[PDB]
Amino acid sequence: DPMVSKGEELFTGVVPILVELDGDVNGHKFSVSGEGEGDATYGKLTLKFICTTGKLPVPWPTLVTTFLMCFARYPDHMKQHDFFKSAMPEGYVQERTIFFKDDGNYKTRAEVKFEGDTLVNRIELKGIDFKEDGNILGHKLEYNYNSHNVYIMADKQKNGIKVNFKIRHNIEDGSVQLADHYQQNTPIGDGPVLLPDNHYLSYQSALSKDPNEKRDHMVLLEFVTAAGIT
Image (cartoon, rainbow, N blue to C red; front, side, top):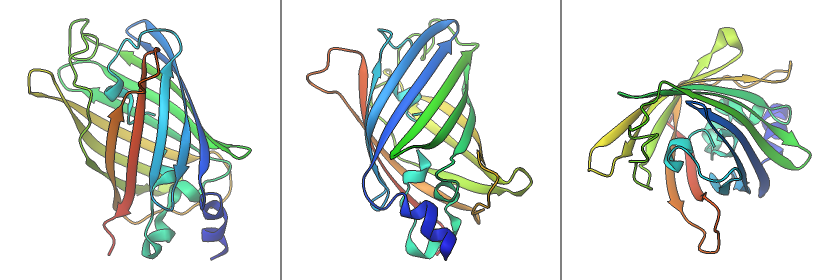
């Protein structure tokens, strides 16, 4: 399939990644840069993020979803359902609203695209209605992360996809902070794209710290595999 060949041919080896985020949560401003690499053959991403403005005013884990679904491993039987790659190199727009239960919300807009050989994820994040002493602005979320299925459906009328999922962030007292994600993706280009049958992506995420890093930061290792169409 000459289509499966193209956007796909972009992802067959290891691909450098750049991430840039401009954040304002309750008038708390911040910027984050990230660098790393994706190997979609194995559904694998390794990135390190740095708050370049000092202290991150929210928990790092609250940002993991926002900080690259084109790096999912789609099984051979499922290649015709990989929207993310199909949109490349021109890229796509990924927009979210993420509702933190009993707290504020983030609204994000991202452009995911190639800049030459580098895959680039440019983000703007606005958070509003947060509690200064909640689990988010009060930094009460543990530095870890649970595995999660993400359910993808076609959005045929917007020539793109809808993604819907919940993330439970562990709180220090042992309870959980629910973060309800609503997502929409649309191609940046005017060309054809693969619009998938309902399926899901399985996410495993591991959060760590660089022992030689003084700045406020996050090392993220994600494995992501498409499933749910046998």
